Image (tube, coloured by chain):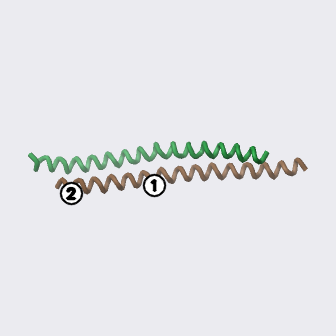
Chain colours: A brown, B green
Amino acid sequence: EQLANARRDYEAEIARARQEAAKIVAQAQERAKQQEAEIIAQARREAERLKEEAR
Amino acid sequence: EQLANARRDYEAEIARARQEAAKIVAQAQERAKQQEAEIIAQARREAERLKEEAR
């Protein structure tokens, strides 16, 4: 009975850790991609506008 | 007593598994916020770097 309980506890703990990692990793990538995309777009718009103004 | 404790251990394993599952979600939410903030901070530096390159 104790061995079966340990097996059930190990499976639940591993699944909980796996679920925790997936949610945390996805949030970091989503936030970084959203933040990085805005960085490139902001510079691209300014560069195009500045080139016409300087000319 | 061991037989009685075995039933208690089986119940303890279920209780510990639920506690770990709640802790995993709590750890994931805390980790995701820090991971997103750290990635945003690096991308914010890149945004200034992209703006500096554009200027």
Q: Give the structural element (helix, strand or loop) at label 2.
A: helix
Q: What chain does badge 1 belong to?
A: A
Q: Give the structural element (helix, strand or loop) at label 1.
A: helix
Amino acid beneath label 1:
Ala
- Both marks 1 and 2 on one chain: yes
Taking the image as shown, residue B44 lies to the left or right of residue B38, namely right
Task: Name the residue carrying label 2.
Answer: A4
Task: Name the residue carrying label 1.
Answer: A22
**Is the residue marked by circle 1 packed among few (<14), some (14-19), or many (20+) residues within 10 Å?**
few
Give the mark nearest the N terminus, 1 or 2: 2
Location of residue B15 in the rendering, given as x and y in whole percent from the top left corner? 26, 47
**Is the residue marked by circle 2 packed among few (<14), some (14-19), or many (20+) residues within 10 Å?**
few
Taking the image as shown, residue B32 lies to the left or right of residue B23, namely right
Residue drawn 18% across and 53% down? A2
Location of residue A34 in the rendering, given as x and y in whole percent from the top left corner? 61, 51
Q: Quadrant of residue B52?
A: top right
Q: What chain does badge 2 belong to?
A: A
Location of residue A24 in the rendering, given as x and y in whole percent from the top left corner? 47, 50
Location of residue B3 in the rendering, given as x and y in whole percent from the top left corner? 10, 50
